[PDB]
Image (cartoon, rainbow, N blue to C red):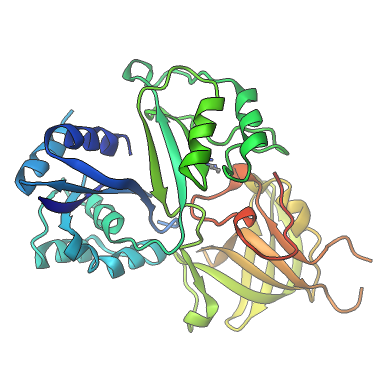
Length: 355
Ligand SMILES: N=C(N)NCCCCN
């Protein structure tokens, strides 16, 4: 009656859970989908209770044989907490992962360099203060790689009935069904929501080709777990994401490609921000900024540039009737990054929500 956490680095995890739940023991609660630093990113972890940890390792390996895997006890699980934090909000080297695995004799399956190990350990050690659920439907093997068939309208009807119990599944303004991937992966669709109830209802209203397997995951998606407040650092750096307050010093200007840039003066000096082309209408908002506007930006730092996920216009330049209204703005659903918390999940005022 041993309780162990499996860390893998989602389809394969589901196949693995299956064999566990049928040949070695049960699975406690909901499996977990953890995303790592978005600038460097998924990894799955699940709690199980078997008798022979060695047996459990034997299974998973066969499954992986038809990649990093870790098997830690609920005990060590709490220790990996910091490793998980650094893997999500900072940068880790595969050395640091090999160290932990070595220090606590964590049984594992290593392949080559073993960069799958960082995710495997991170998935197990991640402590979720906030979280969201995701229902992932899979296709039958026979259809992997072919074109997904589904009724676009059914997803829009579904969001119309469930939103916000389910969210960021479709994009009305840009007319896109964002919960459906366009890759050779086994995933048919991935609906995000606030509960099993809503997700189950969603799965029942949506129309698509026959769904083979399905799994509701607990994830750090849409939580803002990657953001570092500016009161926590002395200097900013690339490959990290922040929530910075600043004052516009250089007004918006477009560049080749449909992107809009500008700069803000901050406790750290001037910082350049951007609203790349995929953000669509969100650029309309950005183009209205003016020298003097005080704001608070949220985003990943890359090449010394904040890649806007959302922004808050705190104060409009003192000396102006402008179109810009104070309050929150965010990229449309189709430009949403996995870890970005959507305004519909934030109990704040002045939220301008684009559905
Ligand atoms: N609804 C989802 N499962 N994902 C939404 C992703 C939006 C950015 N591509």
